[PDB]
Amino acid sequence: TGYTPIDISLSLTQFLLSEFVPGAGFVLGLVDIIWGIFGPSQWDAFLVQIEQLINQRIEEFARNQAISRLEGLSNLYQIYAESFREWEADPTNPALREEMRIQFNDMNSALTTAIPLFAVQNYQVPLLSVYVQAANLHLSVLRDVSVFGQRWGFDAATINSRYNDLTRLIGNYTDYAVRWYNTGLERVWGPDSRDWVRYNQFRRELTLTVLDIVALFPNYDSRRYPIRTVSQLTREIYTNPVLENFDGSFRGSAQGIERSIRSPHLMDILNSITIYTDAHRGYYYWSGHQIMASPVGFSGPEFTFPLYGTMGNAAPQQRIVAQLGQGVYRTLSSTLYRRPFNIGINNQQLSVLDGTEFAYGTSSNLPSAVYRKSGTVDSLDEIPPQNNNVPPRQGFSHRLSHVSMFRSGFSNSSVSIIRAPMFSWIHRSAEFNNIIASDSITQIPAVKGNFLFNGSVISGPGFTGGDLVRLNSSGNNIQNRGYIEVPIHFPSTSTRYRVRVRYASVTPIHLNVNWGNSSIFSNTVPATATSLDNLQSSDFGYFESANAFTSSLGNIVGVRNFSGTAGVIIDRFEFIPV
Ligand SMILES: CC(=O)N[C@@H]1[C@@H](O)[C@@H](O)[C@@H](CO)O[C@H]1O
């Protein structure tokens, strides 16, 4: 059918983001999306997807052993799923209850045996995606026994033991996956542009097929999340048409290309891009541009970034409005390469864009914005739909969040000109606004805030689904306390909410949580980590307000660091309806 593991994973991500609640729906969902296949095809494809990228086939025996085992888990989970489905339909039935207990044990036992075979020495990287899939399924099944095990007829001692497995393995699987993500990525680095392409492709593909899934693992903790919980992925992934459609390779450019990506920041909303046009020998091109953005929820004035590339005057400037409908979901770019037989300042090599169509995500339809012309270098090939059952403009997975630029040469004095817009893509689960649901546990990442004082945004470890907020120590200045404020919106004004914060700290730290002007928590929270530099899964802890309140307290939430000597990492705010 022409599908790749990337398509499949994005679809699974969509599911896990919107349907993360225990019950038959979840179990049947996993069968429908991943585990309902017959035969080795899918699994082979999952392996090839990473193998072809690192340019290394898994040793043949270990490869067949892994594929074979995945087939086994598939058959077994299909049976488990149907037993679950019939059981839910008739929960008091003793025969169904006994069958569930047997099915759970077989499933748990098979997964525990199978997993190390997806961690074979010297082949951890190409086996990573199937590992994560298996790990996901295992956590899922452990979550199921935690929620339903009593009703199935397991004793309290067995349930608690399985739950302790769940919490430990949330940690272990996460750390394993991130470690091997980092290792694999690092191996793929090289000095030239061809290397950078491969490196970024790895980052991109494994973000979509590994990291994105891992980021949702904490959700399986049924005690922490006893009802439906909605996560948001704020991380950005990258395409670059000029570089990615280039068959040659720019020597020693990789570092420069990588630096052209912007550094960690509070999430913004891309409003417009103003493109400047330069020309050479009747070839008109995108020479530079200017970005305009807004804070999350349009909760502040629009801001303008410094000029990217060079301001050319060969044609009038074109202001492309990105923020219409759901925003820009797709770029279709026209690449221009000039490689003349004789090269000189009068006859330059060009590696640029001479057109781009910017297509909008929309429930209906909306005409595309077009810089000069459309092209065939299509972002949808790299950033596919999460839902392939509707048109791409409805079933898209990402939204254009920024455009920066890798640049080389000056038109006036160079033989070779590179102008390579770097397109940055945010997952659509990163909503324009912070909207607190009334019937589910709403997760709002701290980086979705709009005001940060005595602190900085730092790179996530890779398992949080985006970046993190670091509040600095005050230096014993009551006026210099680190503060992050998040704008929030309540569609329901009568629902009562407890506010939970997910954090990391090396020493005990006094934190103050405000909802509007009201302080709803002010106390010392324990240390959770040994280091803030090398973050592992268990380094993140939780604390929460004692009481529940309504939207009448206000439309902001914040955390203040009262410590004079220690810093603290804020991951996300969570709103729990009582
Ligand atoms: C006495 C006190 O804590 N003052 C805080 C200050 O520490 C800082 O957080 C600032 C950021 O806006 O807000 C002030 O209200």
Image: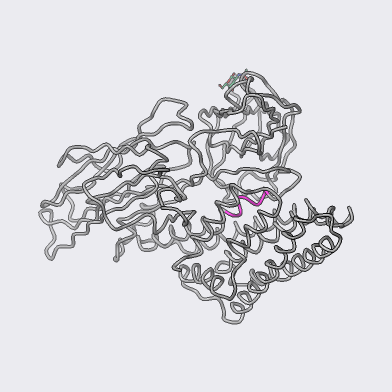
- On the picture, is 423 further left or further right than 267? left
Counting labels gives 0
Q: Residue 324: horizontal and vertical position, in percent?
A: 37, 37
Between 566 and 175, the residue placed more toward the observer is 175
The image quadrant in which ligand 1 is located: top right
Q: Position of residue 313 (x, y in %)?
A: 16, 39
In percent of the image, x 68 and y 31: which residue is there? 499
Residue 442, magenta (yes or no): no
Residue 184 vs residue 227: left or right? left
- Stretch of the chain drawn in magenta: 213-219
Instruction: Quadrant for residue 309, please give it.
Output: top left
Residue at 80%, 57% (x, y): give it.
162
Q: Is residue 218 magenta?
A: yes
Up/down of 342 relative to 371, above or below:
below
Quadrant for the N terminus in the image: bottom left
Q: Nearer the viewer, residue 524 or 209?
A: 209
Q: Position of residue 378 (x, y in %)?
A: 34, 56
Q: Position of residue 553 (x, y in %)?
A: 64, 20
Image quarter of residue 524: top right
Which residue corresponds to the image point at 64% horizontal and 33% vertical from the top-left? Answer: 438
- Determine the residue positioned at 62% across, 57% down: 29
Frontmost residue, 383 versus 102: 102
Picture quarter containing residue 295?
A: top left
**Most prominent secondary structure in the magenta stretch?**
helix
Quick one: quadrant of the C terminus? top right
